[PDB]
Length: 223
Image 1 (cartoon, helix red, strand yellow):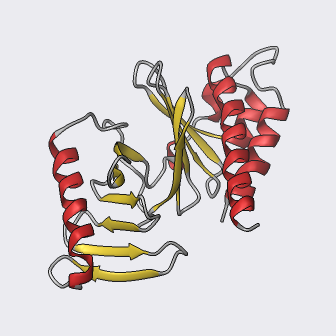
Image 2: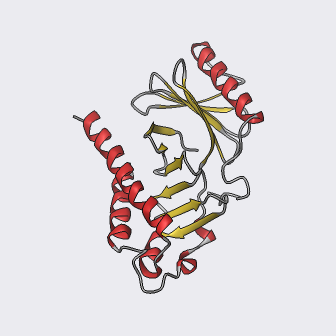
Image 3: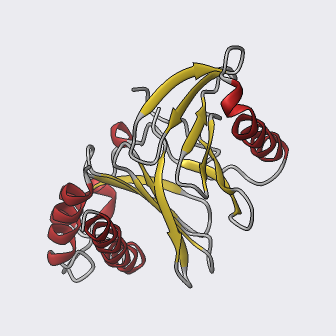
């Protein structure tokens, strides 16, 4: 995956101590060309029985079931992709799907319907850049929920103040959605040059810890 790439990027930007500069010029690091193609707009933790369902900013939906398999539905409302525990992908459609997936497709439909009429869309005011990933894994801490997409992106939504970070190792950029719901995207390399505010800096440090956790978990699974 690209978690190692993200770790290299985060280690470097944090090592630069971006908030400890004579004159922070964060605005110079912003770049709309780096806006993510995808991010999680909504999610529902129904781990008590089925798993975690979620909606991406393009209105597609998906679910990481308790059995570690995934099912995602494109925003066209018919194209489906089933991903087994080990990552094996199968391309299907709602119109023509194997009966073996009836239950999971039904569960995804319930998640889809719920998220279609309930909850706010994170980054609703932002249009993703044009280029479908699935949720590789997720977990919660006492402070936030961490979501890792198959395209390498890692999203961290903080519970207390509703602030969020969307990190992409391909663009080597970070999107920070603040408490006022302002959505700004920065090149990590430019944050090293121009610095940034203490709020973003602190969250980037937390992000590095979360990425280490994700890497540690993968390492454990690989024995």
